[PDB]
Amino acid sequence: DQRFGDLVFRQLAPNVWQHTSYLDMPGFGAVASNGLIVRDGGRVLVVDTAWTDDQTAQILNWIKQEINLPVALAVVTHAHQDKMGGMDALHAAGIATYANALSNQLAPQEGMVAAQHSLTFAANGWVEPATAPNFGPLKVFYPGPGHTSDNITVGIDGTDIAFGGCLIKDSKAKSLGNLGDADTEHYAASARAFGAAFPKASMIVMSHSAPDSRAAITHTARMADKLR
Ligand SMILES: [O-]
Ligand SMILES: [Zn+2]
Ligand SMILES: [Zn+2]
């Protein structure tokens, strides 16, 4: 771990880092949320904002210090604050932003600023390529409704890493976290669909646990079986 102001950064693979930010949300403690930073040749790609604009600007500061290449785009994985709370900071920095069309639709009512561009998805869940131009190694997949109706996931080609966002919790988790906007009927199938989309990913990264093996997926799905 690298502490940088109030955030934490951890290298996961040669061109991949996890960003972590915290929100002291009254009645729950200081909640960590993780996203990703990927160097693709001469540019940087970001998955998820931090909770706030200020924290997200700090992610960009860390990138400037440690990588020193332009951030070409960011993709955010649903319309909750931990994933989209820093959209304004990305826009102020001139970064092109992407989210599930449904996330952009939901953003205002969730108190979020929408991304600039909307991703749409084929019936099988893979992103429609025209809507994710220049995504390089980021392979975006909609696994079905789970943690939220709009949750999306991202594999990183050239690595063993797939990012489940808030859909997936680690193999030791006692709960599925914030289910306030969850789809209880479809959660288990959506967790399993994420696993099936990225079958060779041995490192599973997620919002509210440290990186884990694929047991994160099986355990999450087995816990989600109890929601039905
Ligand atoms: O979330
Ligand atoms: Zn969420
Ligand atoms: Zn979350």
Image: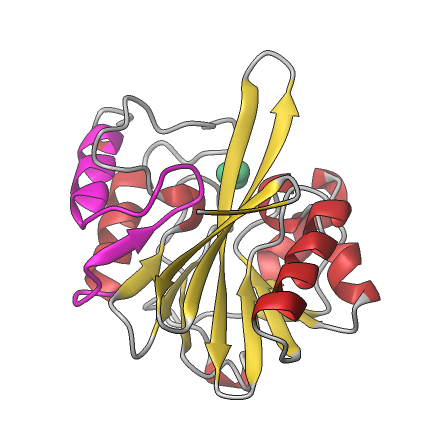
> Residue, x 67% and y 69% (percent of image)?
64
Side of 75 relative to 212 (left or right)? right
Q: Image quarter for residue 226?
A: top left
Side of 120 relative to 224 (left or right)? right
Residue 98 screen position, x and y as percent: 62, 68
Q: In this rendered view, identify the residue nearer to me: 154 or 94.
A: 94
Is residue 186 visible in the rendered structure shown here? no
Q: Image quarter for residue 94?
A: bottom right
Side of 25 relative to 94 (left or right)? left
- Looking at the picture, the colour scheme in use is secondary structure
Residue 188 versus residue 61 in the image, above or below: above
Is residue 174 visible in the rendered structure shown here? yes
Name the quadrant of the C terminus: top left
Count of marks placed on residues: 0
Residue 186 screen position, x and y as percent: 32, 41
Side of 199 relative to 145 (left or right)? left
Residue 152 screen position, x and y as percent: 45, 57
Q: Image quarter for residue 177?
A: top left
Residue range highlighted in magenta:
198-224
* Magenta segment includes 219: yes
* Magenta segment includes 125: no
Residue 44 screen position, x and y as percent: 56, 76
Q: In this rendered view, identify the residue nearer to me: 67 or 198.
A: 67
Residue most extreme to the top: 27
> Residue, x 48% and y 41% (percent of image)?
148
Q: In this rendered view, identify the residue nearer to me: 20 or 191.
A: 20
Q: In this rendered view, identify the residue nearer to me: 215 or 223.
A: 215
> Residue, x 44% and y 73% (percent of image)?
127
Residue 198 versus residue 173 in the image, above or below: below
